[PDB]
Amino acid sequence: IVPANHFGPIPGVPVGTMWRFRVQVSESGVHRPHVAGIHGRSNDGAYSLVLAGGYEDDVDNGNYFTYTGSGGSSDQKLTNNNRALALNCHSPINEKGAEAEDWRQGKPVRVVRNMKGGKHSKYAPAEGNRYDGIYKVVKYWPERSGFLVWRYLLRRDDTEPEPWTREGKDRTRQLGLTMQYPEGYLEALANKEKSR
Amino acid sequence: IVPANHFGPIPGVPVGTMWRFRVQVSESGVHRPHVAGIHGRSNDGAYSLVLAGGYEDDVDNGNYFTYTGSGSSDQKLTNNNRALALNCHSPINEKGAEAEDWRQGKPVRVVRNMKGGKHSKYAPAEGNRYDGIYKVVKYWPERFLVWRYLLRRDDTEPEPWTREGKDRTRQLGLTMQYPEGYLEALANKEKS
DNA sequence: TCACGCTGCGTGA
DNA sequence: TCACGCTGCGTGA
Image (cartoon, rainbow over all chains, first blue to last red):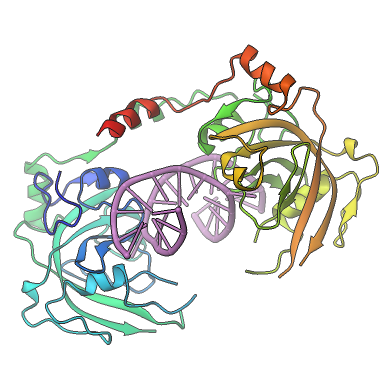
């Protein structure tokens, strides 16, 4: 595997792989937190995040999406994962939001989409978790719920194509990527011979 | 295998049975909720509760303990907290009540989780432990405002922390139950 | 379906 | 240690 604070793609998991649970996504190293949306250290940056349709805003447009941080029922602070993510934007950490001088020079963020994101996004998978590639932070800002939240614009910068495109649907088919289940999960669950 | 809304002990699960995880305690049947403290419908009663030290408002003395409900917001005798109150042998009362002949209330299987050892010597060291049948003696509200219950034990087989009970566990072979493949892959990860 | 809940765990700090 | 948290499940409704 690779270090936890490692930035960028995990070697061997191309764009379009599909795990069923987030523990498989973790063991794969693509997104190490079992539950948390963001993986980051406030002193370094954010290494990976998940879109599971948590926030009633957070508009998902494929190559572009808005995203909201962690905290709170009370105001969100620019600390921990919130601060970690903003560190990737090619701009000095500003406590009032910043924009990127050449956004493509930001730290890379791994991004996977989850079936629960379908509540708000046409780009979610029908099932499980799909690593949709690399994004960079272009902008971040605070806004009002009725409380203050920290939000982020993310643009995609990966060489391999989005899995929902024609080119990407061919990469998913040619590389033979199928929904990967935990060893034993399918076989074990098929046994519903309880009492009746 | 007795329905979900069955009162009293589960056939085949003796007092002192041990499971490492809450999921096996639901497969067992003794306590079907995976997370929730109480199993109970608001017009029938409660079937099982777990002592996992979740609330400041709790005292555990073994043969009896006092228990807390569901809720930084005032509680109500609704849903599960309504359910437990019907297990008391006295008509439901929004002001709290006590049972005359508490032993004719409806049985409640009590599971003890290791997360209660902090404030109870009677909790197990590891995992979960089925400790028999308790009945509701009395229930009342207390100050935020919360609902509390007192539960005495009414089960013929001995408690697993006594001499008689500890003798049943050794002789019945009840040892800590783990999921298949848990110990295998966790020894794997332990050595790394 | 829908929301809840005495979980349980790897990682940041 | 504790803080943290875009899990996941059965459950009543």
